[PDB]
Amino acid sequence: MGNQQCNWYGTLYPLCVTTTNGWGWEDQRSCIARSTCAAQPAPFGIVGSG
């Protein structure tokens, strides 16, 4: 697979690649755009380390 996550200043959100054009809502929850998701600075960024 190859999904990215949003270490949101501490919280965790699923990345909305289609809504990567800003904040979006998918997965029956809130998804944060691509970069807005991970691109953010640390410790913000792409999460998903199983």
Image: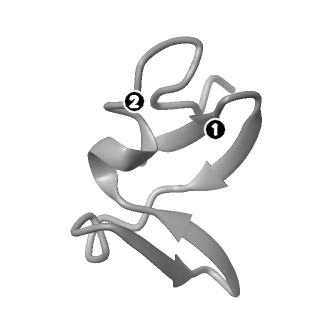
Q: Residue at x 51, y 12 (%)?
A: 42
Residue farthest right in this picture: 11
> Left or right: where does residue 22 sit relative to residue 27?
left
Q: Quadrant of residue 18?
A: bottom left
Name the residue type under label 1.
Trp
Residue 33 position, x and y percent, is 36, 60
Dot 2, how many residues are within 10 Å of its Cα: few (below 14), some (14-19), or many (20+)? some
Disc 2 + disc 1, Cβ < 8 Å = yes
The residue that disc 1 covers is 8
Is there any visible trace of residue 8 in the rendered image? yes
Dot 1, how many residues are within 10 Å of its Cα: few (below 14), some (14-19), or many (20+)? many
Q: Quadrant of residue 38?
A: top left
Q: Secondary structure at mark 1?
A: strand
Is there any visible trace of residue 1 in the rendered image? no
Q: Image height check: is 40 above or below 31?
A: above
Residue 11 position, x and y percent, is 77, 39
The residue that disc 2 covers is 40
Which mark is drawn over residue 35? none
Which quarter of the rendering shows the C terminus?
top right
Residue 35 position, x and y percent, is 29, 43
